[PDB]
Image 1 (cartoon, rainbow over the protein chains, first blue to last red):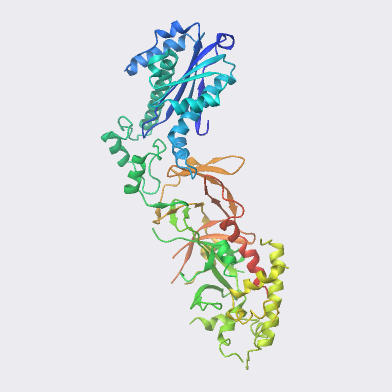
Image 2: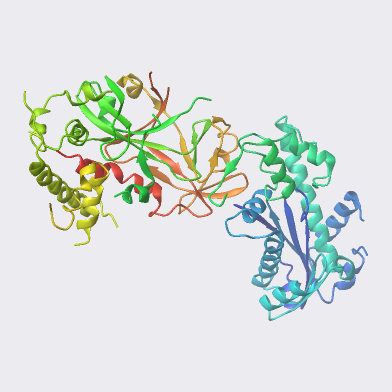
Amino acid sequence: NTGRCRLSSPVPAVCLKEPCVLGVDEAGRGPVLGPMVYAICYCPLSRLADLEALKVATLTENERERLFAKMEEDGDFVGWALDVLSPNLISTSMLGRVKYNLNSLSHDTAAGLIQYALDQNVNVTQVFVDTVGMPETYQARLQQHFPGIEVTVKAKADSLFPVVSAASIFAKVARDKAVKNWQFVENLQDLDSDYGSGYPNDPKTKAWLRKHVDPVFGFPQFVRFSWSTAQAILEKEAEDVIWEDSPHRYFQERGLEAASSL
Amino acid sequence: AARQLVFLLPEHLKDASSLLFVKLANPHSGEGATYLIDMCLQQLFEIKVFKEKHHSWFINQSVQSGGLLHFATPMDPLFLLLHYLLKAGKPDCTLLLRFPELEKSLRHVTEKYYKYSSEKTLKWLEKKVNQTVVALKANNVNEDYVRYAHGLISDYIPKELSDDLSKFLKL
Amino acid sequence: IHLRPGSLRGAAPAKLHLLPCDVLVSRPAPVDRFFTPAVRHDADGLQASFRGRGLRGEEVAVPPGFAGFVMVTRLIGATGSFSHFTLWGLETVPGPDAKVHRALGWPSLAAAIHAQ
């Protein structure tokens, strides 16, 4: 696993011969807490009618789970793959000396999951990717990378194409099984897991982070250190840390000087 | 918590078969510096510090700021004993020179009666440059060494500005 | 300031990390809760994280014929003993031509300068 973690269903045989259509979507782009999940759902152009039903446009946690199992049942034709990204990998990526923002971390993650499908010999002929605002530049980078297929990027994709609507579901469902798994362990180890929504705009989430600042180390793994809310709390609550980027010659070249101090 | 020091001490200091940190005058330039002196085995060591911008230590279950690494490296008392006479030209200072094999070492730069000699010192300092040229070849510090090897002894003596005539022209 | 070989001879092992960052205040810290369980091994040294930043490490040895000690305060006695330490770098392992790796070359040269 290491930083990220990929979970995947075996490729249904139909998908290796029949022309396929693929849907890319995510969950967890925005919280301070927990992972960011990416999901691809693919299915034959012929079997699109079967998915037109399991398509919304909202759908509660219970209904999401139900629709997730309904798709998981019909694994004879619907294929899926997930890449669950840790708050730590998100922290480390964005806090490198080399700038590497969420959007880049996000989309590179989309590229890999679409690439996985290709490497699995899924007869992908058309990809649809959901986005947040202005789809253009995203289509440009994505189409340029995948020149053998049509790549469509629309902000309303989770509402236009059932395959994106399905990818939205696995991603949301995986995002909730991952936070429940952390909560379960938290509670086992008698730790406080009452954070709230997970978003930095939540008074209860803000409160939780404030109650959880080790002066030396800051927060536990779960916290996306790279978030401004996260950083801002560490500036007020933890010890100040200065990083690398915030003859008389020999000793100067090694960093050596005499001890007057002692 | 209390300030923790990170030392690199010679392997032998450990065994008994007695140890004092004495503030002594810096022979090159400076009012003072730290010197560790062996009283049982009767020897001198200088204290250098590794300080580099933005480092700290995790020492066991604690953090120590700064990231300093202190070194106790054997010192030749000849450099430290030079300042008692050097001013003539023709505090803890006391225990510093008084040791066995002192008089036999003193007959290198100076000479009951002790008299400083400029001739012997230049001959001795020139030998050190070559002695440290051997080390710079073994340790491989990145001919051209002539200027560099002379410079290293300058950080131990103020007579190296008077040995700037000893640079290129030997004396 | 003076101290016998007693503290030196009987100093207990200590675990040292040299961070590429300065934690401005000296204090106890739960290294074993936060730090240690983040450390991982691979073909090129170790990986761990601090304040959400990716660090890359390496075990660095105390010079040959030398001994590492942690000393607390006149009189100054040794609290820990080490023979090696972890040298952390940001995103990329500190290079061989780094200030730290150059200081460790000092005792070897110091023996030649001060040789009788």
